Image (cartoon, coloured by chain):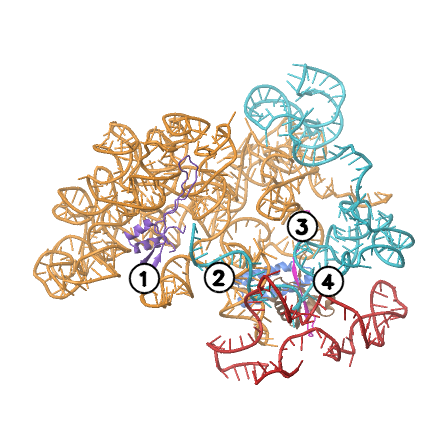
Chain colours: A purple, B blue, C brown, D red, E cyan, F orange
Amino acid sequence: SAHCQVTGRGPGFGNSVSHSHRRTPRRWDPNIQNKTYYLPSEGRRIRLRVSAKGIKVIDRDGIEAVVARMRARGEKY
Amino acid sequence: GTTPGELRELTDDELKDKLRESKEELFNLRFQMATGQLSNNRRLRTVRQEIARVYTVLRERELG
Amino acid sequence: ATITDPRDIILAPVISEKSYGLIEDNVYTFVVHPDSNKTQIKIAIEKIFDVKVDSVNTANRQGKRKRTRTGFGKRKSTKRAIVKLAAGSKPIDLFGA
RNA sequence: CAUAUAUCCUGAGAGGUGAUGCAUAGCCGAGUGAGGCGAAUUCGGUGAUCCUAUGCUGCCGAGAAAAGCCUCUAGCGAGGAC
RNA sequence: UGCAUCCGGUGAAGCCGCCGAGUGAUCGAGUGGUGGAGGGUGUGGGAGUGAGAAUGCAGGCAUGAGUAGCGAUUAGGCAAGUGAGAACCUUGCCCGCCGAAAGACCAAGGGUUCCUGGGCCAGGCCAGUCCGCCCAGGGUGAGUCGGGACCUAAGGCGAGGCCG
RNA sequence: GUCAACCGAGCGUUGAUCCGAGGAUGUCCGAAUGGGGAAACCCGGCACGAGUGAUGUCGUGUCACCAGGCGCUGAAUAUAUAGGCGUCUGGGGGGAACGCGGGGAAGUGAAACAUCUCAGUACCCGUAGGAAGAGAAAACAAAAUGUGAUUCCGUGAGUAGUGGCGAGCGAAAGCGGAGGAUGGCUAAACCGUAUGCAUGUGAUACCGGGUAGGGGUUGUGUGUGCGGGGUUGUGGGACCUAUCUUUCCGGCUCUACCUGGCUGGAGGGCAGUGAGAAAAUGUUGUGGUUAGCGGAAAUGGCUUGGGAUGGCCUGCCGUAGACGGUGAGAGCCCGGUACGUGAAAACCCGACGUCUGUCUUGAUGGUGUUCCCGAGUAGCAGCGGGCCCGUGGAAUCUGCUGUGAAUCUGCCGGGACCACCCGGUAAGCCUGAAUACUUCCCAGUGACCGAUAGCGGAUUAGUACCGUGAGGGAAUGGUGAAAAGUACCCCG
């Protein structure tokens, strides 16, 4: 995928099941979405690819904080 | 017949004088060599070397 | 430094029956550098000999391919240039036939 | 205002020049092959799958684009146009 | 190969042998020819350690065999020629074949095969003075030809970009 | 230079050929990077310079892409932004193995086979380094008064165990060892700060009490960036508050005065290119590497032989009888060895003095309570990976979703779980040495091969030849001591 942006919750690769096994993965994706937000600092609307988890992070942590944390990682937002 | 310390007395424009002269000599030698009017083949080598020395001295004087 | 000399392009004459039949009527064939061209050769010649060129030509030659105990070698290509001096008509002395 | 073979455009070809030249039948000895002079050069028929023809006529299956050419201004504009 | 000793350009090995031996695998420190520099013996050590067969591998040579063939349905010939040597090579006069091709000109493709001089131990399905064979030298010239510097179709690559 | 001769013409004691380190030049393709392109070939721009009567031409440079920093502008559109223009630094690809993270098979074995195994191997991806990764206890252990970062080796152990309890897989603790740095740096409570989004007791508050001008060191909030303080487990730390209180002063604590606390310089100490901040400096070691050089002793005698380096007999050297070559086995012929020498320049080690900081304005202990001890995390549930462990009673370690806590009577572990005791203090970060590996380079060894062997390649070898293409992929060593390679004649 375009890859998460605030955390880095990438995929994973499972395998087997019950009822006798069979070996066979099925990526365990993450739940990213395309929520947008508003930066009152620079007067702008930003769209991101963020999981619901990361939305939780935002609403109990801020957006400025998050973009600074992403600036660190230098994601091409 | 020259050497580097001998040439390093000469300023630039003198070096270019000898440079152009030696190229004229090399040209006339190549025509003589084709025609068969040449025996002392080695003058080609000597001239080619002298040209190299002169360019070398110029570059020394431009990187000094 | 670098100094454009015209005498580094023109490499050598040509010596053969065709060339001499041309010289009998004032056409001279030289061997040049492959990356030359006609304006460059014209300028080189009507500088070197201070004589009045009016038309120039060219040609390319793909070198021969000889054999050896080793195997299949190959000589070098060239570029032959052919000059028709105008009515000025001072023949090129340094040629030496 | 217009229907005119007006006017314009396009356009196979016939004609003059191009060409007092070239070149050609042939002749001369000459022998590897060099050579040199060099006549008349009108008239009719026949006939192209070629040219006008990207034309014309008809039909339906309804038939590349851009550069180039011409043109109108924007503008560079006091120097240059043929 | 460890160790001890013996022979060796006054001729080792290897090979061809002759004469002989061992119950056998094998042996000759028994002698000749060839040939030209390392070998033998006793004891122990270690093995890429013994080939006649794998429709076995590599090279060489036989039987078939001096046999079949020598590549179309056009067809060759006589004189002279140089030459060591001529059915074929050069010339002369005949003859015959294709003639919407077996003729003349381009593109792709190949790459000196083109010309001259010399050459014929290899090659050409015979020979060859000949050849697209061999060697050396020579030779391809563009304002207007086919392309580029002029344009675009199918399609390609694809800044940024979007997806993953 | 050479296979590889021949011919021609030359140079060299004025030091050539040759060897080593540094420089210069360095056509075109290639990450290829001005644009383009069928790889090595086509077309240009801009600044300068050369050149023509002017154009054409020529030469020197430079022009791609992105990421970041800085600078100018801020389109729809108001703030203002994306974007656009200029400049500065990076990255871009190749590599023989070795490493870490991720993905990830199958033939095979099971005398069938799917679970399992082969193997988390081959292969693929992303990134490295000279080594990597891991690494300082939220660990082991068992009541022994024990151990004390990690990694790699030996053993434990083919055991306890796991497993269609079938094939088969398979630890750890513990113990002995190599190497030692039982290593350091941060965040938070709390202050001093610039701030930045807010407001206005618009005042009895901003500070050391107090003598006090103001009338706000903005009055109070709140995150941000900087600086102090603080780095622990038997808990520590910040507030608090006594005690001894191991330098001089400059100014500061809003302010003149008594103290407490800062902001400066100075002797000093400590340390340094360290992991713990970072650059260059100049001395500098017969310290090391990159060419080399000297180097002992028999023309010894007789014979053989084409040639003595052989046999036999005479001498010698030996910090040198290793090896090879020389016309046949050479310690005494040659090359060289044992041994000692040798570096203008460059490179590497430390060594220093520069230079840089850094503690110095300080510490040891006391004493009763509030505050802090790394949050979308740890934990629980649902699917899954891997741990001896195939969902089983199945801990610890973990991946995605969903839900979701506290700060020391706190929390995590000691193979479900609960109570007691024990050990330890997660969710921030760096860390050398032991270890693995060889494209290349240097010097040697061999109970390894000796031309159908040995690297596929002793011979033009990844060549010829084959294939459209990826890709396959051969064959051929020996004259003799030295070419003295048969001059000359005869047949042809």
Toward which corner of the image does residue B33 lie, by quadrant?
bottom right
Check disc 1 and give the amino acid type: Gly
- As drawn, the label of residue C16 is 4
Check disc 4 and give the amino acid type: Ser
Same-chain status of marks 2 and 4: no
- Say above or below: D80 vs F126: below
Same-chain status of marks 2 and 3: no
Check disc 2 and give the amino acid type: Leu
**Horizontal arrangement in the rendering, residue A22 relative to residue F365 (left or right):** right
Q: CA distance from mark 3 to mark 1?
A: 75 Å
Instruction: Name the foreground residue: F124 vs F282.
Output: F124
Label pair 2/1, CB-CB below 8 angstroms: no
SS of the residue at dot 1?
A: loop
Q: Nearer the viewer, mark 3 or mark 1?
A: 1
Instruction: Name the foreground residue: F11 vs E45.
Output: E45
Q: Residues within 10 Å of mark 3 (few under 14, many from 20)?
A: few
Q: CA distance from mark 2 to mark 1?
A: 56 Å
- As drawn, the label of residue C72 is 3
- As drawn, the label of residue B63 is 2
Q: Nearer the viewer, mark 4 or mark 3?
A: 3
Instruction: State which region is magenta.
Output: C68-91
Q: Is residue A31 magenta?
A: no
SS of the residue at dot 3?
A: loop
Instruction: Name the foreground residue: C55 vs E137.
Output: C55
* Residue bearing mark 1: A43
SS of the residue at dot 4?
A: loop
Q: Nearer the viewer, mark 2 or mark 3?
A: 3
Q: CA distance from mark 4 to mark 3?
A: 27 Å
Same-chain status of marks 4 and 3: yes
Check disc 3 and give the amino acid type: Phe
- Mark yes or no: residue A52 visible: yes
Considering the whole magenta stretch, tell me its main secondary structure: loop
